[PDB]
Amino acid sequence: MSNTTWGLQRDITPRLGARLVQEGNQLHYLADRASITGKFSDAECPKLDVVFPHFISQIESMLTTGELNPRHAQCVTLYHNGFTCEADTLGSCGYVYIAVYPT
């Protein structure tokens, strides 16, 4: 599976899904768990690549403050340059599930 059960249940399309690995307060990207559902326009692609790293930092920052808790499932909605990102640990104590799509 390139997607995740949680990611397959998202509704908005197109979307970029990924399950990141949490080391301390650092989120690691794993391509084997990254996927695109639907399709982004040629214009959105480079744009999405620029906003992705910003969502990651936002999320790492939320794990430090506690807003995001590895032990408790709780979804958050983030924004950045016309894009939205839903992120949730699902209380996995090690993973952070995300979905990025146009607002």
Image (tube, rainbow, N blue to C red):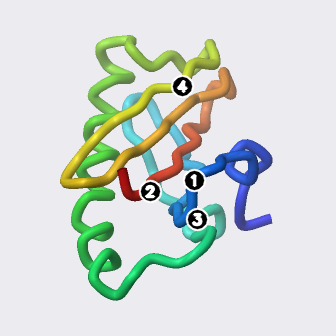
Q: Earlier in the sequence, mark 4 or mark 1?
A: 1
Residue 72 versus residue 78: which sits nearer the camera?
Answer: 78
| Amino acid type at image mark 3 | Ala
Residue wearing tag 4 = 75
Task: Give the alpha-carbon distance from disc 4 to disc 3, as whole Å.
Answer: 19 Å
| Amino acid type at image mark 2 | Tyr
Q: How packed is label 3: few (under 14 Cα within 10 Å), some, or many (20 or more)?
A: some
Task: Give the alpha-carbon distance from disc 4 to disc 1, as whole Å.
Answer: 15 Å
Residue wearing tag 1 = 12
Q: State the residue at coordinates (52%, 61%).
A: 15
Which is closer to the viewer, label 4 or label 3? 4
Q: State the residue at coordinates (19%, 54%).
A: 81
Secondary structure under the numbered disc 2 in the rendered image: strand
Q: Tags 1 and 2 in contact by the CB under 8 Å rule?
A: yes
Q: Tags 4 and 3 in contact by the CB under 8 Å rule?
A: no
Q: In which quarter of the image is the N terminus?
A: bottom right
Q: Which of marks 2 and 4 is nearer the N terminus?
A: 4
Q: In which quarter of the image is residue 32?
A: bottom right
Secondary structure under the numbered disc 3 in the rendered image: strand
Q: How packed is label 4: few (under 14 Cα within 10 Å), some, or many (20 or more)?
A: some
| Amino acid type at image mark 4 | Cys
Task: Give the alpha-carbon distance from disc 2 to disc 4, as whole Å.
Answer: 15 Å
Residue wearing tag 3 = 34
Residue 9 vs 102, above or below: the answer is above
Q: Earlier in the sequence, mark 1 or mark 2?
A: 1
Secondary structure under the numbered disc 1 in the rendered image: loop
Task: Give the alpha-carbon distance from disc 1 to disc 3, as whole Å.
Answer: 16 Å
